[PDB]
Amino acid sequence: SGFRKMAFPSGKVEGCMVQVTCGTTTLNGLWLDDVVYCPRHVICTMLNPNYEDLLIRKSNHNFLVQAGNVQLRVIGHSMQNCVLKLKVDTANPKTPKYKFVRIQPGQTFSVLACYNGSPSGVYQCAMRPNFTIKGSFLNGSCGSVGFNIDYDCVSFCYMHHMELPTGVHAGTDLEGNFYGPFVDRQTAQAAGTDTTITVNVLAWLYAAVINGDRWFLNRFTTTLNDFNLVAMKYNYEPLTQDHVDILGPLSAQTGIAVLDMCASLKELLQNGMNGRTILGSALLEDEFTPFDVVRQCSGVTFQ
Amino acid sequence: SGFRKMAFPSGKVEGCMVQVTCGTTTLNGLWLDDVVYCPRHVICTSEDMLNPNYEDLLIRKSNHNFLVQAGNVQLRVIGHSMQNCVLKLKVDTANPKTPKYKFVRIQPGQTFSVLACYNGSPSGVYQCAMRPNFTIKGSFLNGSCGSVGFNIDYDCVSFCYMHHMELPTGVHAGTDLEGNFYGPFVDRQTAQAAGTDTTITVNVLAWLYAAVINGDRWFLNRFTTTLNDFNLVAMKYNYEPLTQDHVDILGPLSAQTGIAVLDMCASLKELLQNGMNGRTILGSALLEDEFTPFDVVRQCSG
Ligand SMILES: *C(=N)[C@H](C[C@H]1CC(C)(C)NC1=O)NC(=O)[C@@H]1[C@@H]2CC[C@@H](CC2(F)F)N1C(=O)[C@@H](CC1CCC1)NC(=O)C(F)(F)F
Ligand SMILES: *C(=N)[C@H](C[C@H]1CC(C)(C)NC1=O)NC(=O)[C@@H]1[C@@H]2CC[C@@H](CC2(F)F)N1C(=O)[C@@H](CC1CCC1)NC(=O)C(F)(F)F
Ligand SMILES: [Cl-]
């Protein structure tokens, strides 16, 4: 038993991480097959950069790419949105089975924080409703990646590009499209007002009941419309029928209907915790998806 | 900036995990060079779990009784030895993925990364602290035993924990990689209980320093304290004593923030007296004790 914030095993991604140096800027790149993916702001020397014009002036030899103590030869460069693609002479022999996916707000992934192309640590993040992540990133962290594992397949969903003034983080998918209304430029930008990921809070309350924490359960049920009136008032994301459907398994297992669990959450929002905890937390946690709870409580493995 | 419960990258440990089967019992083993380390209770039967004579059970075992699997490859056991509560299975093939490694016995308050495994395959990685009562707050299901706790210094894996048991309060106990249990626990089904747990005071102070480095000062105050006056208050909230060693260890974080250790001790004293009053620190409504001074410096300073 027990319940922890659990990251995916990072080994398949560790063997893809390289160092990319251009001018004075060093950051990380992702080496898959014969291409290194990294943030395009590596070329910058910043208020209003013309990325296409700056890239035309670059040659292949301007990009120093190192896999450990081995220099890779760049034989081509191209920009895809906010991501630079450096074609190299060698295919990565450690390339895992992979694909590029775009995640939706409320989805979780594992971040492999890297410095100088060397993996430093791994942690679990949720894409916030305001399209930021609450990461942990120092100088040289950019090009660190976020992923999920399904069977033997790494799904890359995030590359790290920037920190906003409130100390939260923003980046792109591996096709270089920003999550949220951000640009890779030194100009005034702010994270929007954030909201709580309601479906994830319910999943975590189900996790609490599976681990024998039940003091918040009650006799009452609510309706989706009445719950959503309360959700709106407390800066919670609307609960949809899709969310109710996805919580179906945990509803069946615990014998607590989703709208019955919604009646518990409604009371917690109105009345607070009353000095009590849930799974060692004095607040409602929203960075576990229904699937995160099932895979941790079932012991799904990755080979 | 930012502050997260951060594990070490698990790849160097993933390449060491194997499956070990004896009879109907399957658990995990750690394959380093030509030795597989696993919990000795793999040799136990359901009849004899209250009072197993491990020496007597092991002499009865043949090498072919031990089914060891690395992916889709059976390893041949050519020798076995028991060191304390750990079984060392000598195999014919050395692990080509063996990293640079050390075995270290850690002290209470020390943190490490757990690679939770089933059937020799990794499920996930998370951070744990060795609690003052010599338990860890893990996440472990049937077949999790032989999962290891580790830290990585540069390219070198320090193995500090092997998972052996769950206590009736749902917390976890295990051994170092020489097979010595942390705490008074034994690998037997006989009634055992964790002692009363206490909060790792030096770790709470490290975390308050992390909060200041991340630009939060709301909990600070104008007061100082003596070490003995701090300890008399902390004890009443079931906090571990703060020693001069702990004050010395917090020296670097004190230098960076310009907050004297005994000044930060006065802030924690007030937080214990008042609570947080609808505020959070680093996204938490409680005082977090599972970050060491060392964890804070590597995450906040590089
Ligand atoms: C990648 N290495 C860095 C981000 C890391 C470094 C640190 C410590 C600030 N936190 C990180 O996550 N990426 C950047 O620094 C990016 C690049 C280069 C400069 C600028 C624009 C960019 F996207 F091209 N940038 C930022 O992160 C700036 C963005 C400003 C928009 C309003 C903030 N961030 C900052 O300057 C700061 F200090 F607010 F975080
Ligand atoms: C390793 N696979 C398991 C422990 C995992 C399985 C689960 C779900 C209980 N949680 C885990 O972390 N190890 C054991 O089961 C050990 C072995 C075999 C039986 C017994 C003694 C042992 F150490 F040799 N054991 C236990 O974990 C028992 C210990 C009892 C003494 C007081 C409890 N635990 C339990 O029976 C229980 F239910 F409390 F967790
Ligand atoms: Cl230690």
Image (spheres, coloured by chain):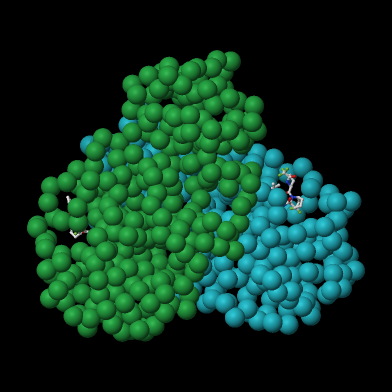
Chain colours: A green, B cyan
**Residue B72 horizontal/vertical position (percent):** 69, 71
The residue sitting at 11% across, 63% down in the picture is A50
Q: Is residue B299 left or right of residue A162?
A: right
The residue sitting at 69% across, 60% down in the picture is B119
**Residue A259 horizontal/vertical position (percent):** 52, 22
Q: Is residue B148 above or below residue B216?
A: below
Q: Is residue A57 left or right of residue A159?
A: left
**Residue A274 horizontal/vertical position (percent):** 46, 21
A252 and B30: which is toward the camera: A252
Q: Is residue B301 left or right of residue A222?
A: left
Dividing the image into 4 quarters, which one contains the N terminus of chain A? top right
The residue sitting at 48% across, 61% down in the picture is A154
Query: Which residue ends up furthest to the left in the rendered image?
Result: A48
Q: Is residue A15 left or right of residue A172?
A: right
The residue sitting at 52% across, 70% down in the picture is B12
B55 and A61: which is toward the camera: A61
B188 and B273: which is toward the camera: B188
**Residue B76 horizontal/vertical position (percent):** 77, 78
Tell me where residue A143 sits by quadrant: bottom left
Is residue B232 shown to the viewer in this render? no
Quadrant for ligand 1? Answer: bottom left
